[PDB]
Length: 209
Length: 41
Length: 48
Length: 49
Image 1: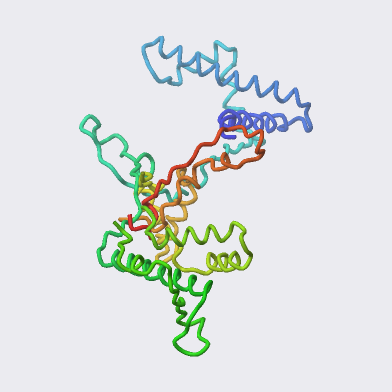
Image 2: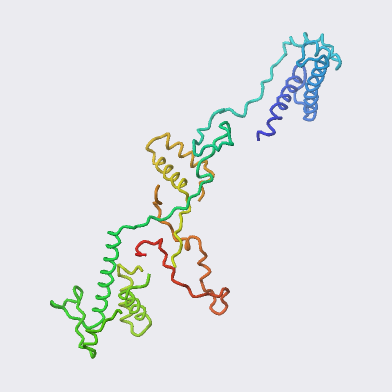
């Protein structure tokens, strides 16, 4: 979680500092509540020279503090500043490393490059570009229509030929049949002649009228 | 849209062959339905 | 009575996107593949 | 892509609740059914009109 790592990268650096300052001419294996006590007094001490040396310089109409604003800030906290050049030149002096950076890759994204659409004149050019079509563009689409007279004539012709062939083979198979050749029922079956009782009636009369 | 008389007659014969007058006409009607190429429409 | 001519559930920008992504993902060029693979890996509207 | 390379699917099969025409109990049938008119869908090819 990088949210609490904004605070814990610098407070757990102050925990290594107190653990390095309690080892210099001193302890090993301290109590746990005694370390979070002392690193709370350390954070509250840096934050108090921050607020008071800024207040002493801004009282003198300035914005960034000089040396004369901190040697009056440390006097008002009771520090005895003169003992500090001797403390800085220890042989036990140690350096605690700064915390690591979350964005170690920095630039690891190939990205997704998509451009479509422009800007209406109430949006200047420095605003971000309008995104791609899939985000908000919808058009219905239909099936490919075959309006060709050649293939429509071919379709109607072949369907009529196939249905009349199927009808005549079904009627020749389920009735009396003839065959121009010998024992020929599978290939070219003929519906047998039927002397009717309605002669001229089935010849001369129209059926579609 | 309306069936032509050819396929209207084919529809009539095929449906009335599967109502139960005899079994042989039913078997030939089902072998027609299963094995014809143009029965769409 | 004829039922209305239906439309495909993809847009033509979406259908063109599908055609470009599939013709890039058959790997004729490697940079084309890699973007198309990242596009598959993070397009939010790649459902439907 | 001027036209779809995937045929427009049957919207009724893909979307409609045809499950509502199943007749679970003949006597106690929940929805009163009605005669259906022929609709001759023109999306299907192989039909002249």
